[PDB]
Image (tube, rainbow over all chains, first blue to last red; front, top):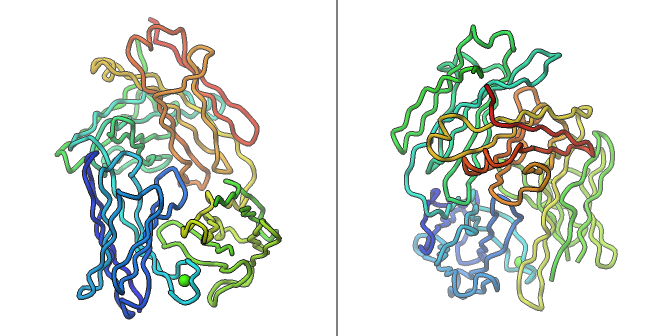
Length: 224
Length: 206
Ligand SMILES: [Ca+2]
């Protein structure tokens, strides 16, 4: 089959460069053009440029001119994309996308799986685990919401459980935000009965393996 | 040079929906955990393998993707695409999120958490606005310092599906310990399907 295999996720400092690979199999490598298209977390698809693997000639998008370099290796059937002088706005999933040369019209038939590139000034850092003290969700329904703020960590991922995996009902763990500081932050919340507050203990178990940070944080009810 | 499509379109199961792209137009469907797939090429061509409920048309500068007998599984991002020959460049529309309204309206419950004692020890303060049990999965969040809008230090997550199939969202306001003590109160304002739910928190008094 036609298959496009991309290189693994990468973490980069601002000003640095990244080189993403796209290994093609299952078709005659030099017979089809290869494009690169990115998608930033809070944006649409963005075209970066095109390479013709027969001869190696390139045409780049205006906004990436002087910043992007596309190459190919015919012997390994691999297309490369290099993006230099990285900035936080370059945080995106990068796709290679194949294009049939017949017609002239640029459109895509087969894509790679995508490569996440994260551009951040941050180095490896464990999260601080702050309690989110139980607060009334519904006074008629008799529910309270409590949680943990898993703040200022790098890189992804982090694991959150409650009461060492014993509590799953009404648990919601949010996707992380990448803050302006270049550090991640997420929350995990539990909807509990109000009547369980002060009898039942609630502990969020936070594990961030890159920073060897394992924290078990008890979330106590509000009291003067 | 520029393709314009609405950010949001919705419809109920079994109904017909249209997505407009205004500037040959090609349409891509983006489902999570999968590559973009071509549904329509050259305005009207449906490739082999694409279900017959998808169709494309074009009148003048306006291209349209239509889905008849809408299914819940058609919920996805839809992108229109062109080849701008004057600049020799691929142009994409901004994307249209298609929502399939498969359950009734449910208003969000909003819970606003003050900064923890522990965070304040570290000379920081974060306010956490938890938004839960809403449908459909779209909200607007606005933060307030007393009455005035807060324009910085805000991070908000795209709505995620809960285990009960309703949606949840979170928003964070970063501030200094002094700001938390300066103002009388801070507010989280959530807008869902025209309706506004607001919550306020103040420093604990004992
Ligand atoms: Ca072509």
